[PDB]
Amino acid sequence: GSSGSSGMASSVLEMIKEEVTCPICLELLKEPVSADCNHSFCRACITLNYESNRNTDGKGNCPVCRVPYPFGNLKPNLHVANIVE
Ligand SMILES: [Zn+2]
Ligand SMILES: [Zn+2]
């Protein structure tokens, strides 16, 4: 036979997932907060979204699943770590 080749260095960046990103602003979640519906949003977004769209009853609605979640009961999604067992 007869053939040859050389070295090649070509990598790719992280594939911006269109699932984790904020379903509202579609940008890096800044100090987001998880919700009952395992849905987190920009500390601000979540706040505004609620104000703009709220239920006369008192609670609001998720801009993704539209589920009634108790405001304030939001956990910080900043310490997103697991391997730290
Ligand atoms: Zn946002
Ligand atoms: Zn949701």
Image (tube, rainbow, N blue to C red):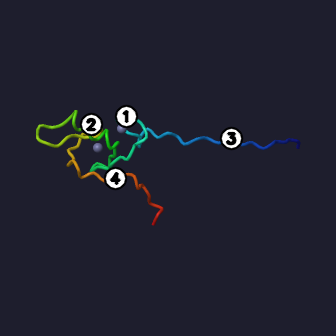
The residue carrying mark 2 is 48
Disc on the earlier residue, 2 or 3? 3
At which x and y percent is residue 47? Answer: 26, 40
Residue density around tag 1, few if under 14, some if 14–19, many if 20 or more, within 10 Å: few
Real-space Cα separation, disc 1 to disc 4, in angstroms: 18 Å
* The disc label shown at residue 76, or none: 4
Disc on the earlier residue, 1 or 3? 3
> Taking the image as four quarters, which one is ligand 2 found in?
top left
- Residue in the image at 78% along x and 44% along y: 7
The residue carrying mark 3 is 10
Disc 1 residue: CB within 8 Å of ligand 1: yes
What secondary structure is marked by label 3?
loop
Disc on the earlier residue, 2 or 4? 2
Number of numbered discs visible in the structure rendering: 4
Disc on the earlier residue, 4 or 3? 3
Residue 1 horizontal side relative to residue 84, left or right: right
What secondary structure is marked by label 4?
strand
Q: Which residue type does callout 3 highlight?
A: Ser
Foreground mark, 4 or 3, reads 4
Q: Which residue type does callout 2 highlight?
A: Leu
The residue carrying mark 1 is 25
Please name whichever residue, 58 or 1, is drawn nearer the observer in this view of the structure: 58
| Residue 53 quadrant | top left
Q: Quadrant of the C terminus?
A: bottom left
